[PDB]
Image: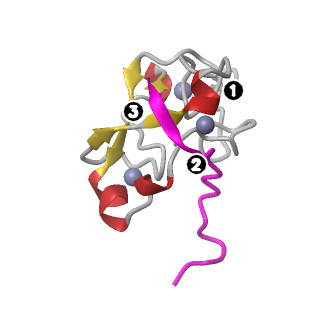
Amino acid sequence: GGSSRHQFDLIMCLKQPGVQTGLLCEKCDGKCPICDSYVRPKRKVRVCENCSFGKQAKNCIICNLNVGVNDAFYCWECCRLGKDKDGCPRILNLGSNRLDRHFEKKKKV
Ligand SMILES: [Zn+2]
Ligand SMILES: [Zn+2]
Ligand SMILES: [Zn+2]
């Protein structure tokens, strides 16, 4: 099941997490970086030092643009599966289309 056109394309940084916690902008607030399903959290996401000392530290990890306000938490489901154990949860895949394929009269995000 899966391993095809159900990837989600969660291309994330996945390096070695540092001390700096991954911040979410209110627009991605509540979203689990690994899956995005507004489900029970568990542990604050740690961004890799490469990102911490790489300018992209305070800015939201999910939409890597707007500054983050709340630390992201890995959802229990991702923790159970063991996706969080990979590393830095910075979403890289997101160049545009914050979610799905709709801006719907909201600039783009
Ligand atoms: Zn998750
Ligand atoms: Zn990183
Ligand atoms: Zn965001």
What is the magenta segment's predominant secondary structure?
A: loop
| Residue 96 on the magenta span | no
User: Residue sitting at 69 percent across and 20 percent down?
Assistant: 107
**Relative to 19, 5 lies left or right:** right
Residue 62, picture quadrant: top right
Which secondary structure, mark 2?
loop
The numbered disc on residue 72 is 3
Q: Residue at x 67, y 45 (%)?
A: 101
> Where are the magenta residues, as a range?
1-22
Mark 2, other Cα within 10 Å: few <14 / some 14–19 / many ≥20: some
Nearer-N-terminus badge (1/3): 3
Q: Does the beta carbon at disc 2 come under 8 Å from ligand 2?
A: yes
Q: What's the amino acid at mark 1?
A: Lys
Q: Amino acid at mark 2?
A: Leu
Q: Quadrant of ligand 2?
A: top right
Which residue, given by chain and number where applicable, does mark 2 sit on?
14
Q: Earlier in the sequence, mark 2 or mark 3?
A: 2
Which residue in the structure is indicated by mark 1?
108
- Pick out the residue farthest to the bottom: 1
Q: Residue at x 57, y 21 (%)?
A: 57
